[PDB]
Amino acid sequence: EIPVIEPLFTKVTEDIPGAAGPVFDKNGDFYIVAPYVEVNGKPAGEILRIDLKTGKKTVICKPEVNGYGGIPAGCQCDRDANQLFVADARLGLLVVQTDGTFEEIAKKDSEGRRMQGCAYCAFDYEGNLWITAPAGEVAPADFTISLDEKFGSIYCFTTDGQMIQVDTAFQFPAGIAVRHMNDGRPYQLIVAEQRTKKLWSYDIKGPAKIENKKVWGHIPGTHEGGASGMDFDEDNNLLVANWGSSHIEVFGPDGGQPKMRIRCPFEKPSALHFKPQTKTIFVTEHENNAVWKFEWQRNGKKQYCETLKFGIFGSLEHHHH
């Protein structure tokens, strides 16, 4: 029904338990997270730097708060400083410096509620951070995932430093991406509900202001698991890892059904991310606990963490003259 392409995948690294959160920082260094690392049967997840020339893996941060180890599950870099925002299914949302120190951004949200554990996040170009939270309350609450009960939530961490819960009642909310229009403005928030075959959209009307929740797209397949991570290319096609499959789905800007599929040499892609200024997509996957790369048909969308650089700054917004 749908065209399938089969690009050459190249293995980057392997033996990363629960491999996810591929991300590039402001300098082009590459990081991933290993959520399933354990010590004595307890979480001890890791944030890793991967040297793309040598393949060498370096543990950047082994987060823990009051003796509760983390489950780092997704990442985005900051443009303002060379620090990573790490969605942690046990600890919430962390800011991790490249030197390994970290700060937990929130024990509680804007309503005084205990924070939920997070997994993916996405900046809009105005600087707000949109976050999926598939786990229940952070440590020291007992760990719970919204696999069977609809308690996964969505947050927005605004430029004013407010952690606002903007929706809930999701069954493993996973990938999240912002659709920016040609004038640079945030228009739609896209959210994967991984325990269904659905992608949801909201219209962004401002910081932490979303409305008009609708079904945006449908994920093919009848196996366990749907959309995990997702990313826009420069034409606002959305590439969506289908964890219940060996494909990445390609949606047009207006969603619906995929218009093309990318066949992968592996099952269970968990996350994907473009390398800045390239067509190269890095993909994490849980069949092999591994990281791969492949060349897409065009560039990715300009990334938040490049937006203060000469040659990028000033080129995102466009207006009538």
Image (spheres, rainbow, N blue to C red):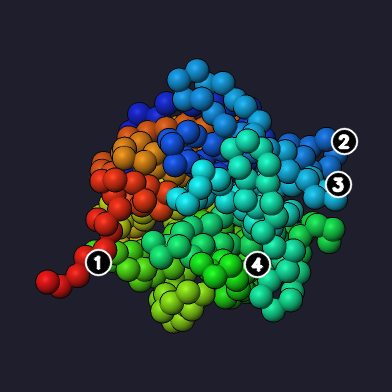
Viewer-nearest residue: 168 or 307:
307
Q: Circle 1 is placed at which residue position?
A: 183
- Left or right position of 43 against 264: right
Q: How far apart, in angstroms, are the residues tagged by discs 3 and 4?
A: 25 Å
Q: How far apart, in angstroms, are the residues tagged by discs 1 and 3?
A: 47 Å
Q: Circle 4 is placed at which residue position?
A: 152
- The mark nearer the N terminus, 4 or 2, is 2
**Amino acid type indicated by mark 1:** Asp
Q: Are marks 2 and 3 in contact (CB under 8 Å)?
A: no
Q: Circle 3 is placed at which residue position?
A: 67
User: Which quarter of the picture shows residue 262?
Assistant: top left
Count of marks overlaid on the render: 4
Q: Are marks 3 and 4 in contact (CB under 8 Å)?
A: no
**Amino acid type indicated by mark 2:** Asn
User: Which quarter of the picture shows residue 169?
Assistant: bottom right
Residue 147 sits above or below residue 165 on the image: above
Residue 18 sits above or below residue 183 on the image: above
- The mark nearer the N terminus, 2 or 3, is 2
Residue 34 sits above or below residue 309 on the image: above
Rendered residue at 44%/56% (across/down): 220
Q: Are marks 1 and 3 in contact (CB under 8 Å)?
A: no
Residue 287 visible in the current orientation? no
Element assignment for label 2: loop
Q: Do the residues labelled 4 and 2 touch (CB within 8 Å)?
A: no
